[PDB]
Image (cartoon, rainbow, N blue to C red; front, side, top):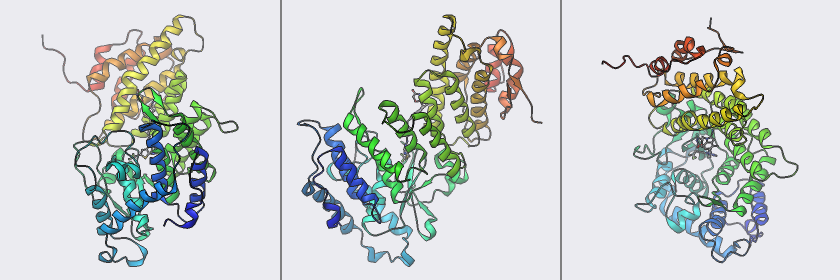
Length: 468
Ligand SMILES: Cc1c(CN2CCC(Nc3ncnc4sc(CC(F)(F)F)cc34)CC2)ccc2c1cc(C#N)n2C[C@H]1CNC(=O)CO1
């Protein structure tokens, strides 16, 4: 509007005042995405970007917020003439969606660092003419809502955002860029990406937001970071309280990564009476299994990271094995590089450092060590099996000799008598391999001294050894 009822809580003088505003908007027919994003971006700017003069909370006065809102709606309504795009049946056209995307995109500063923090909100769009990639998609949806286009909604994968719209909400349209050097397909569907079984489009099991989930997205998008080593306590608490509000209203039910975000916040500072982080990570995994065919990677990564921080080697390895069992049914495609990076870092840095400490503690007499548990060895094997199966039939390889050295080292952290106890069973502690690489590695996995050269040959499918 702003409508009179949206104005009565101002000025916002505290975190709890902001929560009351989110609660009022979430109780409305449609929560005002533009209003809420401006408020979050305002508060984040003066709690994380520029804290000069801060005495408690940056008071958000109505005159300030209303002027920003007016700037946004004047820009959108001046630039998008709806009479040029007749709406058949309350649904938007592809040309109208592309026009709004063009308006947002064409407003952005010509050159700036797209990976900077604090450029996610409409506050950054208005005051700095800067948005990150998914911020552009959110802004398109907010502009569409301001124009009355009730059918345009945010669509989210684990590393990209676009919009759905049109009859039955069945159309998709790219509205922003993805990655760096990748060239944008703004205005096109996501059907080629779904058909190629890339992780980026989740085989079609991506999130189709309603307006309440779009509120949850902007709340996840809060960035409490002040710099490398310092977070805003105020912004952490604000994001935590807003996630619990959404949780209680049922709006995180279909949002796995938001549940993992909330679990991370509870780990940092638990709220009395609320579920433990572990309960929340498992709800996030349950959400992915229930609504998204268990095709999401990050619910298991959230869990693994928690167990990693708590040096629970057994449970971290189980969660990473489960991450690999999801990825194995994808094809590794160009533009999936973010998930390749995460698996690379887990295999080649995080697991080695975890097992190195476990080895030292074993030498110091620890009991019940993961390194003496055959089920833990099986989890390590299943992790590599899913990565090898991922690679099968992909248009580009995954493994190379730079993975082989760490595999050999991690295998060797388990004594031969532990590795011997895993029974590897063929279809048609027990483990079945899906990948041909790990099936051929089976015989090598139980020798007292692991044949490092033969392991490397099998993992990289290297044909030959050195001539001389
Ligand atoms: C937990 C976590 C994170 C945190 N992320 C925060 C942002 C979350 N994203 C989103 N969240 C909510 N909504 C959306 S909507 C959307 C699409 C968009 F809209 F943006 F396009 C994205 C997105 C995804 C999770 C990173 C790496 C993690 C883990 C855990 C592990 C392990 N194990 N790892 C790998 C390790 C490897 N090595 C290391 O040293 C340390 O990390």
